[PDB]
Image (cartoon, rainbow, N blue to C red; front, side, top):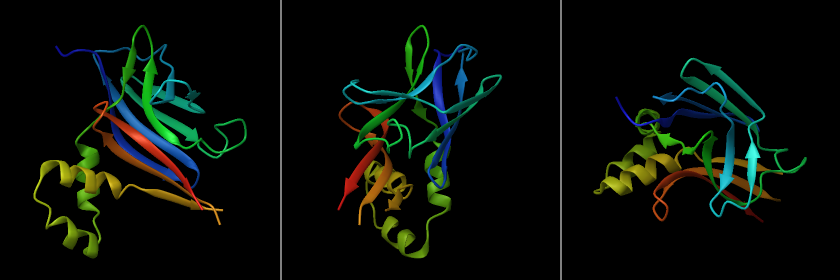
Length: 159
């Protein structure tokens, strides 16, 4: 009934392993290839593992080694299923709700002063930020990139 689509249902980390759970609508995943692709499409990194159960998928990316034993480079990445077409993963609203349900008290107090839909969405996605310290700080934060109108992972490296 709906156009072929890929959705992200949940994002979480097990230390340096990034997991993305989701599902497709009107799209067989049997010959799918899930990748992170940067905004300019000059770099594509395949998932280290993909498990498919019917229309459900779970992707694992070992972010510490995706670049030939080094960490995923600083960039903005889309999650793409590369089949007959390239299907860019869409965020399921569940991800937004889960962020809201897990706000901490100080976060909740700041969130409650927000007045715009876009501000609320941006705030909630930013609570997913994951930071590694090795002093180099490596942060991975999801967002809706307004320019290309897509969910992305923003990877930023700081000293």
